[PDB]
Length: 375
Ligand SMILES: CCS(=O)(=O)N1CCC[C@@H]2CN3CCc4cc(OC)ccc4[C@@H]3C[C@@H]21
Image (cartoon, rainbow, N blue to C red; front, side, top):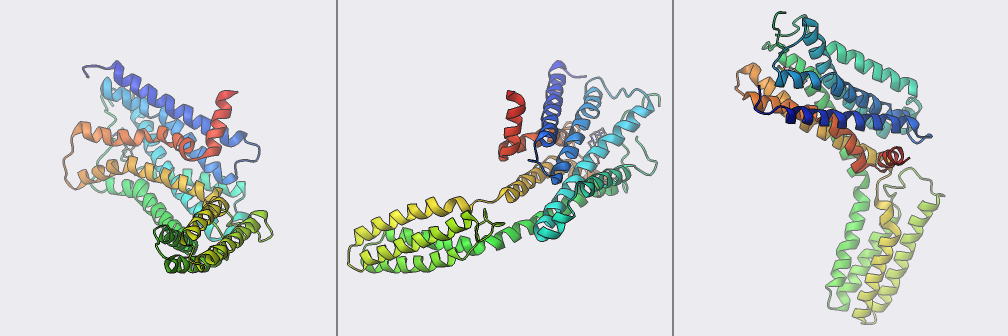
């Protein structure tokens, strides 16, 4: 059917190998670590097990129907083929939605939800998501469309809408509405410390380009107020630490040292020694960066929620134009055949793009993959 064929099937086999290899590496990395992975990561193996299931049981049949024609072998072929092909996409979307709800509840109610985060509760959520995904994916007896039954799903004007908002749109909307609240909560929690940090930076730049003792003295006084205010804050890395913790003591003592160096710089500035005060300002800038800047980072939980956020973003980016045009055809809109094919082709390669996100943005997953590969 195509001018060249071996190139496309080698491409698809390359894609299937990447999906299987990456997702089975994720599953092994999650299950083999000695208390390094939590039950809240059980969803990551279900989403991974779905990606493997979509690489060995979904994309090869579509590849064959694309090159050799839609030669489905039996009516049960298109039946289970379209059923599992929609089930895996629906289960992936609802798994991402349940993950976003898991992060939201773990943030809002730490102690309470941590007590209800048992592996039994997580396994029950996974089974429930799989069950409701199989229910939503199952159509009301309108299966497809047995001599030459091309695996082309039915396109009812009022079934396309139900299936799309039941699989993609509702989970994506809910998970987006969840992560925007996660983003707002994080920024509201770090706003005051970021304000004090930006005040310290602006007054340091003022002293950098200052030319008289009045400017540097004023900036140092405002820095003293900013440093004392930031000292009473809780940095993002130490968000779950005690006041007697050595890092919290180091954070407090670091701003104590910064205030002391500001007092010394003010003693220099009041004597008219502008250049000496500016040099002391550069020294306390380095001291502040060396003492505090490591605590401005997020903890492991916040970094992983960001990783799951960009995973949701990749999932939406891969599947949105497909559902968008597939819904547009229901209300009377024209789309090219090759373009309409490549739109869900972007959704297929999401299964292989999912494991590599962990290697890019996470250090534990990348270390576990390196450990499995090296030894
Ligand atoms: C040519 C008819 S098709 O275009 O329908 N073709 C049938 C074979 C499988 C192909 C890829 N799968 C990806 C998952 C998916 C989910 C849907 O709702 C969630 C709806 C369709 C599909 C498509 C159908 C597509």
